[PDB]
Image 1 (cartoon, helix red, strand yellow):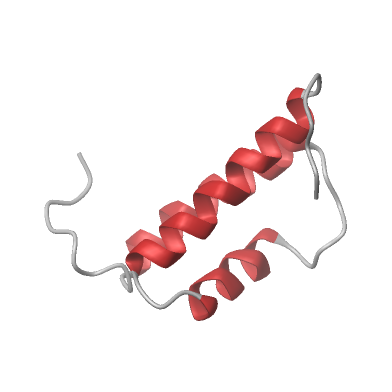
Image 2 (cartoon, one colour):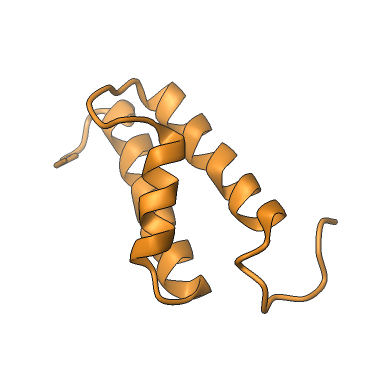
Length: 77
């Protein structure tokens, strides 16, 4: 798989993998404004209080991206 535990979201592998996801969704999402994925993920982390807060804000971000590019929906940035 990838990992067994779940009490170390501060691990490089963790943030790393997540960073790639956000970068992938954005790419296919077709957007441009903020600094960059790396910068976006970094902010979310420092903005989060726990592995949940981050994983939460991250998911919403990725999902919102898929919708914007998905079209035929609301999509409000």
